[PDB]
Image (cartoon, coloured by chain):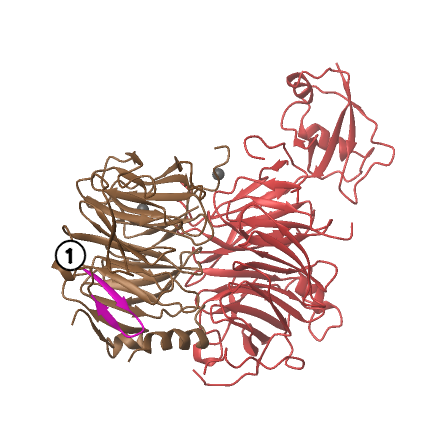
Chain colours: A red, B brown
C-alpha cells in the first residue's frame, strides 16, 4: 500500500526542478517523514530544515492515507503537496519594564529598515551584530533607547526640556542617527541620537512639527528619501520632512501661544484630510516611495499619491479599520487591514473583493508587521492582550459568515498574567517583527520579546 | 441574523479608576472621547478605544449626568453635580488653541431660577468656565441639537423642576410650569422645535412655539425610569422600574405600540442610536444591557419592526445595582455602559 505524491512550493530558494515526481510510503507518514524526505541528499540537500505541508490550502496534521481515507478519496490518486518552511516557535525570552503603558516599539538592526537605510551612503553607522537598539515610546511622554540585552542607554528629555508635552502614540527609527515620534501634543518630533563610548546616549529634539489638529495615532518613516507620514484622529494624513533644511513654516495658530530651550518649529510639506472618520494608519509603499496607503475608521483604505495631493484609489471595507501594513507580493503589494471587528482583511489595492480574512483575534487589531524571512507570513497584535502569527498559505472556505479564511499558526500571550476579559491590563498596542524578533509593547507596561 | 448587522456583541474595552459607581457616560460629538461622571464627584475624559484616561476634574457631591455640547465647533462638556451645572473645556488632544478659544468665546458670550457664575480660582484653572445654580438637586440634563439651549430637570424641585437654559444670554427660565407630578427627565425634539417632559406616570410633549401642551402619551408603567426620542422624531422608547420596555409610535397612538420584558430587574436607562442605525439598547439593574434592532421605515403606512439582537453581560452587580447608563457612538455601532462596578465598558 504505497501512495504517489507531488511537491509544490512558494518558497523562492527551495525547489526541485524535475524532482517534484515522487512515490512514497504512506505508513505512519506525517510532517516528520516527508520533511526528512525533502531534506534528503536526493532532493533539497538542506538536511536540517523543518517543513510543513499544505494539501489544497490546508496543513496536514494527520497520516497521509488516513487523510485520503477520511475524505473518501481513492488510494492510488496523487496528492499535490505544497511545502513551506515551518515557523520556528517564538517562545518567551525577555521583558523591558516601563513605568507606564508602552505605546510604540521599533528595532534598529542590520536587517531592520533603519539599519539598511543607515548602512547605505552612511552619514550614519551601519549597525554591528553586537549593537542592536530597541526604541520604546510610552504614555509617560518618554522615548527610551534599549539595549539588545534590555538595558536603558538613553531616555528622551523631560517635559519642559523639549520632549513631548503629552503621551507619545507612535515612534520609529528613520536612521541610526535620527528617530521620529508623534503623540497627543499634536506634534511630530524629530530627534538626533548620539551614543557615548560607555553606554549612555542623548536624544536631542531636532524638529517640532505642527500640522495636525488632533492626536497623531500613526507614524511611518522612510530613511532614504528622508520622509515621514502620519495618520491622525482629525481624519488627516500628514506628509513631513525630518530635515530643518527643507521645511515649510508652521501654521502658527497650532503653536503653544516649559520654554527652557528652543528647537526649530516647522510645518508639513503636505497635509490632506481624506477621511470622514479618524485616520488610523498611514504607510509608505514598500517599493514606490511616492505612493502611500491610508486606513481609517470610515472603512476606507486609500491609495494616495504623495507627488500630488491626489488620492488615486479608494477601497471600502465592511468595518472601521484600526491598522494597516503592506506585504510585498507582482510590482504592487498586498495590504493587511486590522479591524475593530477583530478580523484582518487581506486587500489588493490593484484593479472590492477580499482575498482572505484572518480570523480568531478576540478584540481590536491595533498593530501589524510582516515577517522578516518568509513573507507569506505576518504578525498581528491586538487589544485582547495577544500577538498572533499568521501564514497566508493556510486558507479555508468561509462557513457562517463569508471568500476564504486563515486561522492563526501561532499565539503569543502576555507572560505578565484565564486570559482577562476584554483587554483588561493586557492590551497590546504595538508589535514589530525583526530577526531578533517579535517585540510587543502594551498596557501591561512592558516590551515583551519572543524568538526561537 | 440574516441582515441585522452590526450589533454590539462583546466588550472590547474597560475604563477604570472611578472609585464608587459610575453615574453617567457621554461620547464625544466627534466620537474619539468618552466622558464619565463619578460618584467620587469627578468628571473624567477618556480615549475611547484604548481606555486611557486623558483628563479628570473634581467638581464637588456626586456627578449625576454628563453631556457634551452636540456641536463639533466646540468640544464643550456639561456636568451636573449636586445643584450646580458645570460647563467645562476638557484638556484633550482634539483641543487646539483655536478650538479652545472658540469654545471659550461660546461660554463667555453673554457676560434667580439659575445663577451663572465663574466657579472661581482652582476650578477655572482646570478648564471649568461656568457654574449654574438652581434651587433643587439636578437629575437630568439635555441639549438642543444646535447646542444653544439646554434643559435641566430637578425632580424634587417642585415646579422649578424642568428648567430651560439659553447659553447666549446666560438665561434660565421655567416655562409651562404646570405638570401632573414629579418630573424625571426631559428631551428636545430632533427635527421640530418641540419639547418632551417625562413624569413618573406619563410623558408630556409641548411646543416651544406656543409654549403649551401638544400631546400627552401614557406608557402604562408604575414609575418611569427614563426615555429617549428617535432621530426621526415620530417614535420614542420608554423604560421603567416595572422591568418593562415600551415602544411608542406617536403617529399611531398615544399609548405604547409594543411592550418587552427582557429583564428581571429595574431598567435604569434607555437610548436610541442617533445618526442613522436601527439600534437601541436598554440598561438594567442586573448587569446586562439588552440590545434591540428596530427600524422606522420613515415613509409611513407600515409599523416599525422590533427584534432583540443581543444581551450584553459582564457588568458586575455591585451593591444592589446594575448598569446605570448607556451612550452610543455617533457613526459606528459601538455602545458604552456605566455600571455600579466603578467602571465604564465599551461594547462592539
Ligand atoms: Cl482564543
Ligand atoms: Cl470586574
Q: Place residue B151 in its image quadrant.
A: bottom left
Left or right: B198 in relation to B271: left
For this rendering, which residue is in front, A153 or A380? A380
Left or right: A169 in relation to A26: left
Q: Residues within 10 Å of mark 1 (few under 14, many from 20)?
A: few
Q: x, y percentage for residue A347?
A: 65, 47
Q: Which residues are magenta?
A: B162-173
Q: x, y percentage for residue A108?
A: 62, 63
Q: Which residue is mark 1?
A: B178
Secondary structure, magenta segment, majority class: strand
* Chain under disc 1: B
Q: x, y percentage for residue A361?
A: 51, 43
Q: Is residue B248 visible?
A: yes
Q: Is residue B315 visible?
A: no
**At 81% from the left edge and 39% from the top edge, which residue is drawn?**
A15
Q: Is residue A216 above or below residue B247?
A: below
Q: Place residue A393 in its image quadrant.
A: top right
Q: Is mark 1 within 8 Å of ligand 2?
A: no
Q: Which residue is most to the right?
A: A18
Amino acid at each position: 500500500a504505497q501512495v504517489k505524491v507531488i511537491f509544490t512550493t512558494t518558497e523562492p530558494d527551495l525547489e526541485l526542478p524535475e524532482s517534484k515526481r515522487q512515490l512514497l510510503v504512506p505508513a505512519d507518514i506525517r510532517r516528520y517523514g516527508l520533511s526528512r524526505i525533502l531534506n534528503s541528499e536526493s532532493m533539497l540537500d538542506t538536511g536540517s530544515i523543518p517543513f510543513d505541508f499544505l494539501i489544497n490550502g490546508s496543513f496536514l496534521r494527520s497520516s497521509l492515507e488516513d487523510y485520503l481515507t477520511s475524505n473518501g478519496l481513492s488510494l492510488e490518486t496523487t496528492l499535490t503537496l505544497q511545502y513551506v518552511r515551518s515557523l520556528i516557535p517564538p517562545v518567551y525570552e525577555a521583558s523591558f519594564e516601563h513605568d507606564d503603558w508602552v505605546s510604540a516599539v521599533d528595532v534598529l538592526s542590520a536587517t531592520s529598515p533603519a539599519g539598511r537605510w543607515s548602512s547605505a551612503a552612511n552619514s550614519s553607522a551601519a549597525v554591528q551584530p553586537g549593537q542592536e537598539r530597541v526604541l520604546s515610546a510610552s504614555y509617560d511622554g518618554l522615548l527610551r533607547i534599549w539595549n539588545a540585552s534590555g538595558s536603558v542607554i538613553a531616555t528622551s528629555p523631560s517635559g519642559s526640556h523639549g520632549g513631548h508635552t503629552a503621551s507619545i502614540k507612535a515612534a520609529k527609527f528613520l536612521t541610526s542617527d535620527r528617530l521620529a515620534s508623534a503623540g497627543m501634543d499634536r506634534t511630530v518630533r524629530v530627534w538626533k541620537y548620539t551614543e557615548s563610548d560607555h553606554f549612555t546616549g542623548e536624544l536631542k529634539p531636532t524638529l517640532e512639527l505642527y500640522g495636525h489638529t488632533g492626536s497623531v495615532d500613526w507614524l511611518d518613516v522612510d530613511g532614504h528619501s528622508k520622509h515621514i507620514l502620519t495618520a491622525s484622529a482629525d481624519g488627516a494624513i500628514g506628509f513631513w520632512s525630518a530635515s530643518k533644511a527643507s521645511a515649510p513654516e508652521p501654521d502658527a495658530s497650532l503653536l503653544p501661544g516649559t520654554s527652557s530651550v528652543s528647537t526649530a518649529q516647522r510645518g508639513p510639506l503636505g497635509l490632506w484630510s481624506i477621511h470622514t472618520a479618524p485616520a488610523t494608519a498611514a504607510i509608505f509603499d514598500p517599493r514606490d516611495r511616492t505612493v502611500a496607503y491610508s486606513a481609517s475608521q470610515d472603512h476606507t483604505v486609500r491609495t494616495l499619491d504623495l507627488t500630488t495631493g491626489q488620492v488615486v484609489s479608494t477601497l471600502t471595507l465592511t468595518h472601521p479599520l484600526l491598522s494597516l501594513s503592506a506585504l510585498t507580493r507582482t510590482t504592487s503589494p498586498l495590504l493587511a487591514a486590522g479591524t475593530s471587528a477583530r478580523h484582518i482583511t487581506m486587500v489588493d489595492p490593484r484593479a472590492t473583493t477580499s482575498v482572505m480574512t484572518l480570523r480568531g483575534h478576540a478584540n481590536k487589531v491595533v498593530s501589524l508587521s510582516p515577517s522578516p524571512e518568509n513573507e507569506y507570513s505576518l504578525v498581528s497584535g491586538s487589544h485582547d492582550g495577544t500577538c498572533r502569527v499568521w501564514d497566508l498559505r493556510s486558507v479555508r472556505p468561509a462557513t457562517k459568515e463569508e471568500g476564504g479564511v486563515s486561522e492563526p499558526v501561532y499565539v503569543i500571550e502576555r507572560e505578565s498574567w484565564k486570559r482577562p476579559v476584554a483587554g483588561d491590563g493586557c492590551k497590546v498596542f504595538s508589535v514589530v517583527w525583526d530577526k531578533l524578533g517579535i517585540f510587543s509593547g502594551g498596557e501591561d507596561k512592558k516590551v515583551q520579546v519572543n524568538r526561537g | 441574523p440574516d441582515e441585522l448587522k452590526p450589533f454590539p456583541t462583546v466588550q472590547q474595552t474597560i475604563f477604570r479608576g472611578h472609585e464608587g459607581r459610575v453615574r453617567s457616560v457621554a461620547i464625544d460629538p466627534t466620537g474619539v472621547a468618552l466622558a464619565t461622571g463619578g460618584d467620587d464627584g469627578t468628571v473624567r475624559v477618556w480615549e475611547l478605544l484604548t481606555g486611557r484616561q486623558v483628563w479628570s476634574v473634581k467638581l464637588n457631591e456626586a456627578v449625576n449626568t454628563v453631556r457634551w455640547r452636540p456641536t463639533k465647533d466646540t468640544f464643550i462638556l456639561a456636568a451636573a453635580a449636586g445643584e450646580d451645572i458645570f460647563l467645562m473645556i476638557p484638556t484633550h488632544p482634539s483641543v487646539t488653541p483655536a478650538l479652545d478659544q472658540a469654545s471659550r468665546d461660546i461660554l463667555n458670550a453673554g457676560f434667580p431660577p439659575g445663577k451663572w457664575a465663574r466657579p472661581g480660582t482652582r476650578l477655572e484653572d482646570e478648564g471649568v468656565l461656568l457654574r449654574i445654580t438652581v434651587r433643587s438637586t439636578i437629575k437630568a440634563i439635555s441639549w438642543h441639537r444646535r447646542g444653544d439651549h439646554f434643559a435641566t430637570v430637578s425632580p424634587s424641585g417642585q415646579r422649578s423642576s424642568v428648567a430651560i437654559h439659553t447659553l447666549s444670554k446666560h438665561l434660565t427660565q421655567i416655562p409651562f410650569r404646570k405638570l401632573n407630578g414629579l418630573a424625571q427627565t426631559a428631551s428636545f425634539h430632533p427635527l421640530r422645535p418641540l419639547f418632551f417632559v417625562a413624569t413618573q406616570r406619563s410623558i408630556r410633549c409641548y411646543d416651544l412655539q406656543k409654549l403649551e401642551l401638544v400631546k400627552i402619551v401614557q406608557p402604562g408603567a408604575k414609575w418611569i425610569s427614563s426615555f429617549d426620542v428617535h432621530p426621526g422624531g415620530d417614535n420614542l422608547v420608554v423604560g421603567s422600574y416595572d422591568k418593562r420596555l415600551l415602544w411608542h409610535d406617536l403617529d399611531l397612538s398615544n399609548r405604547p405600540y409594543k411592550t418587552m420584558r427582557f429583564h428581571t430587574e429595574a431598567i435604569r436607562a434607555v437610548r436610541f442610536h442617533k445618526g442613522g442605525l436601527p439600534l437601541f439598547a436598554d440598561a438594567s439593574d442586573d448587569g446586562s444591557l439588552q440590545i434591540f434592532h428596530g427600524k422606522v421605515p420613515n415613509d409611513q403606512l407600515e409599523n416599525p419592526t422590533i427584534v432583540p439582537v443581543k444581551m450584553l453581560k459582564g457588568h458586575k452587580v455591585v451593591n444592589k445595582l446594575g448598569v446605570l447608563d448607556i451612550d452610543w457612538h455617533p457613526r459606528e455601532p459601538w455602545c458604552v455602559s456605566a455600571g455600579a462596578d466603578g467602571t465604564a465598558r465599551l461594547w462592539m
